[PDB]
Amino acid sequence: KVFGRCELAAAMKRHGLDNYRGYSLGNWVCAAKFESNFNTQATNRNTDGSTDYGILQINSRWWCNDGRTPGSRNLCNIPCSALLSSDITASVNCAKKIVSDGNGMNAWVAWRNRCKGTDVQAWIRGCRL
Ligand SMILES: [Cl-]
Ligand SMILES: [Cl-]
Ligand SMILES: [Cl-]
Ligand code: NA
């Protein structure tokens, strides 16, 4: 599923991401835009052989099991395919674990390089929340 901007903002707010660990909603929408272009089915392979999955591009090196990343962890206790669903619940619940691990949203390279320090509230402007 490719979400609209405000559709995704509303879904993330319903799932408790607004101000989660101090990150306002616009941060999460900005991160999803640049990680996946709002596409739940996005996948991208990393140099080390791991793969990033879904709207927030969560990495099989640490967070999910895809059966093909030897020596990796599965800290969210889910198959990586669950992160491609049109229902964002699994991605949001796993993202909550990632952001709480000590590095905040710096875990998402696109957030650090394209959202951090910008006017992220612009990403939720006009949306009915
Ligand atoms: Cl915001
Ligand atoms: Cl594996
Ligand atoms: Cl933080
Ligand atoms: Na894994």
Image: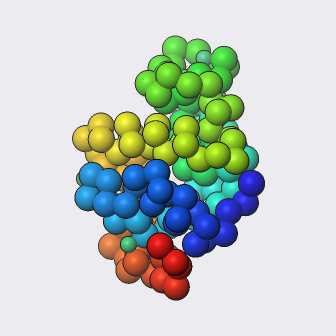
Q: Position of residue 101 (x, y in %)?
A: 30, 37
| Closer to the camera in the image, 21 or 101 | 21
In-front residue for pair 37/72? 37
Picture coordinates of residue 99, whole percent (x, y): 35, 45
| Above or below: residue 86 compared with residue 36 | above
Classify 48 as above or below 25: above
Residue at the outermost top position: 71
Residue 106 appears in the rendering? no
Residue nearer the viewer, 57 or 1? 1
Q: Is residue 18 above or below residue 129?
A: above
- The answer to which of 129 and 95 lies nearer the viewer is 129
Q: Residue at x 26, y 58 (%)?
A: 22
Q: From the viewer's perspective, is residue 97 above or below residue 42?
A: above
Q: Going 64% across and 46% down the picture, which residue do you hit?
A: 87
Where residue 51 sits, quadrant-wise, is top right
Left or right, 100 with respect to 88, comes to left
Label count reads 0
- The answer to whether residue 92 is seen in the rendering is yes
Indicate the quadrant of ligand 2 in the picture: top right
Rendered image coloring scheme: rainbow
Which x, y percent locates residue 125? Answer: 48, 83
**Quarter of the image with the N terminus in it:** bottom right
Name the residue rendered at 55%, 38% in the picture: 90
Q: Please identify the quarter of the rendering in which residue 54 is found.
A: top right
